[PDB]
Image 1 (cartoon, rainbow over the protein chains, first blue to last red):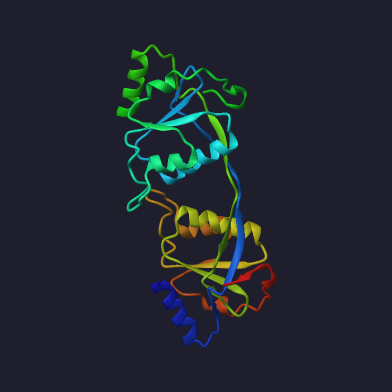
Image 2 (tube, helix red, strand yellow; image 1 turned 120 degrees about the vertical axis):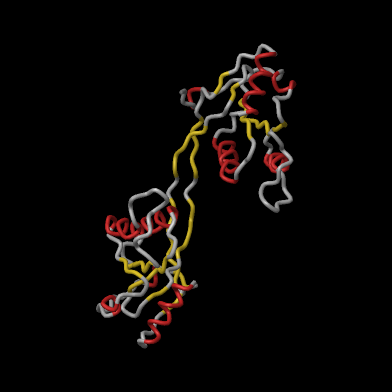
Amino acid sequence: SGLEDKVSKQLESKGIKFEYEEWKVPYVIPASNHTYTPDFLLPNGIFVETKGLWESDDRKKHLLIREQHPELDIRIVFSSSRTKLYKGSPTSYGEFCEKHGIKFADKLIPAEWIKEPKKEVPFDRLKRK
Amino acid sequence: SGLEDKVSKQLESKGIKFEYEEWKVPYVIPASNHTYTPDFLLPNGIFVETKGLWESDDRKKHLLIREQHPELDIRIVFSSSRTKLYKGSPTSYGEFCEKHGIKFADKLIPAEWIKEPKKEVPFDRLKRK
């Protein structure tokens, strides 16, 4: 940077010996608690989230929720699952979902999902509104 | 949204009783591990970070570092300590530092800091670049 150079030029001019970016300090960012509210809950126990732009954080949230709540069946309906993860990415929302076993579809809830046999939803583990 | 509207219309048209944003799924964002590399380390054991823009995440980082490594003396030299935290915020970088006990200066490292008596830095706690 320009700032680092000024400071650097300062110390040297005054003959101050110093160390630069020589040392690393470890630290941990504490685990945090959050909640996610799926857009729709179908009678057969299927949760459905609708999504246009699907940002990095949101993808991680889904991967985390699947790891933490494997008995939850949460699927996604995209305006377009072809959209690429980011600017010049080669990977698309749909591809990502396929890689992680996230069931998805475009524009509307597929007819077959609505018809899957109802399953138990662990509501005790959830918090209402 | 167009997507939430179309999907709920599709559901209503098929007679599906669905709950909308009725349930909160709790989840945890895992603790993460990092390392911070101060820009300079003076002979007397004082570390100095040079900062221009200083974002919300960078600030939060500084507080975690002070908490986890209270044995280190980490100070900040800003391009301007008058800069506001974020657009609209009334609080400046300099006021954030005073509120949290972080020593700071503007543009160049204060001569009086350079002159403070040496304090041994516990390098066993740190990791070389």
